[PDB]
Amino acid sequence: GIHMGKIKRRAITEHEKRALRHYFFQLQNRSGQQDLIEWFREKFGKDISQPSVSQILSSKYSYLDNTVEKPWDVKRNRPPKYPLLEAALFEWQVQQGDDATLSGETIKRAAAILWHKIPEYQDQPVPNFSNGWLEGFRKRHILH
Image (cartoon, rainbow, N blue to C red; front, side, top):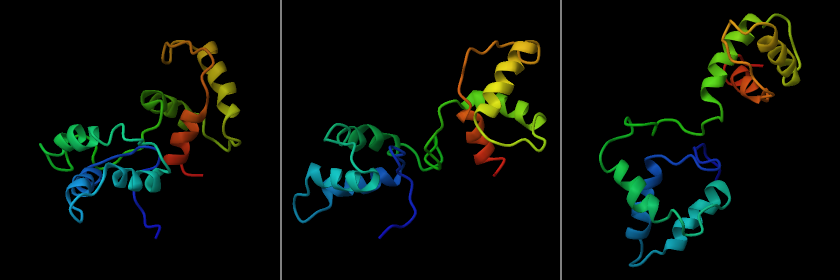
């Protein structure tokens, strides 16, 4: 019924292809491009109006047609927005951990004052970036 898979917005992996190829190719004679979308709409709601159905059939299907689930990132998926920012914004948080609390602005204050008061630690005068990148790692690594 529910089960635990990847998907979520996009995701896409190896099993997404293996099942896709068997989709249009493994049915009672003739499946249907729509059927593909059927698992698309049900997996993430709906985001494949026959646009990538061909791409994932050929392109993404070729990627996994060359190697196994250990090539690029077939293992995991759903990537954040700021990969390098989090790593660097981490090292600062850890040091500025303490009994702190209230995620979000808690950084925008520390960050905006972190790079303004000391531009030698990293040497990157940020403008007005958000704090979600921090919360992202702080939640996906520093727990609650």
